[PDB]
Image: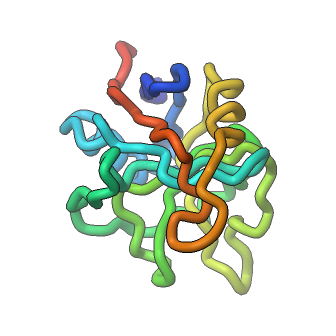
């Protein structure tokens, strides 16, 4: 039932299983970007070793692709940012998520919805290629300044494809 998406990256393949019942808006928004080729030639622009990898915002030359309007935050769905989950990145406002996402390489309780924090909405999980996500998190990065956490050699999503049901 739940849709699967294959991210074919320059570092290996990652397959995601998206949670349509617990994050319908987030899953539909992500699928629209995947199906329209938006994630093709985007990078994992920020990585933190053993903790997270973030992508879905920038080309190899760091130009930010213009995303669609933002979506409602579904972090009150009860899904936690545990190792292997995929969640929507956003700015200060809870309803500001657009195309950027992050894959949790460790359990990040600080990203979870609570009574005083709206949190980051989890909408799926890695079902194959978690070793690729771990490897991407460990690549050499620029260390200080505006490019802190940016991989020194671009990690590119060559294609993002919804798989047959």
Asked if residue 15 lies left or right of residue 37, the reply is: right
Q: How many marks?
A: 0
Point out residue 144 in the picture as x, y percentages from the top left corner.
64, 69
Asked if residue 26 lies left or right of residue 14, the reply is: left
Residue at x-position 48% and y-position 37%? 155
- Examine the rendering and report whether any part of residue 28 can be seen: no
Q: If the image is split into quadrants, where does the C terminus sit?
A: top left
Residue at x-position 77% and y-position 58%? 108
Q: Nearer the viewer, residue 115 or 16?
A: 16
Residue at x-position 42% and y-position 75%? 95
Asked if residue 106 lies left or right of residue 151, the reply is: right
Q: Is residue 103 above or below residue 115?
A: above
Q: Is residue 107 above or below residue 73?
A: above
Point out residue 140 in the picture as x, y percentages from the top left corner.
65, 44
Point out residue 87 in the picture as x, y percentages from the top left corner.
56, 53
Residue at x-position 73% and y-position 75%? 114
Asked if residue 84 lies left or right of residue 160, the reply is: right
**Residue with the most extreme top position:** 164
Q: Nearer the viewer, residue 101 or 155?
A: 155
The colour scheme applied to this rendered structure is: rainbow
- Examine the rendering and report whether any part of residue 130 can be seen: yes
Q: Is residue 68 above or below residue 84?
A: below
């Amino acid at each position: 039932g739940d849709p699967h998406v294959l991210l074919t990256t320059s570092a290996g393949n990652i397959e995601l299983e998206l949670d349509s019942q617990k994050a319908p808006v987030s899953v539909q928004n992500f699928l629209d970007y995947v199906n329209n080729g938006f994630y093709n030639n985007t990078t994992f622009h920020s990585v933190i070793p053993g903790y997270m990898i973030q992508g879905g915002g920038y080309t190899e030359d760091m130009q930010q692709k213009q995303p669609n309007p933002p979506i409602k935050n579904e972090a009150d769905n009860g899904l936690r940012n545990t190792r292997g989950t995929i969640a929507m990145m956003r700015t200060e406002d809870k309803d500001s998520a657009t195309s950027q996402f992050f894959i949790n390489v460790a359990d990040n309780a600080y990203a979870d919805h609570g009574q005083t924090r709206y949190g980051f909405a989890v909408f799926g999980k890695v079902v194959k290629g978690m070793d690729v996500a771990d490897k991407i998190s460990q690549v050499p990065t620029h260390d200080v300044g505006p490019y802190q956490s940016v991989p020194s050699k671009p990690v590119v999503i060559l294609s993002a494809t919804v798989l047959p049901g």
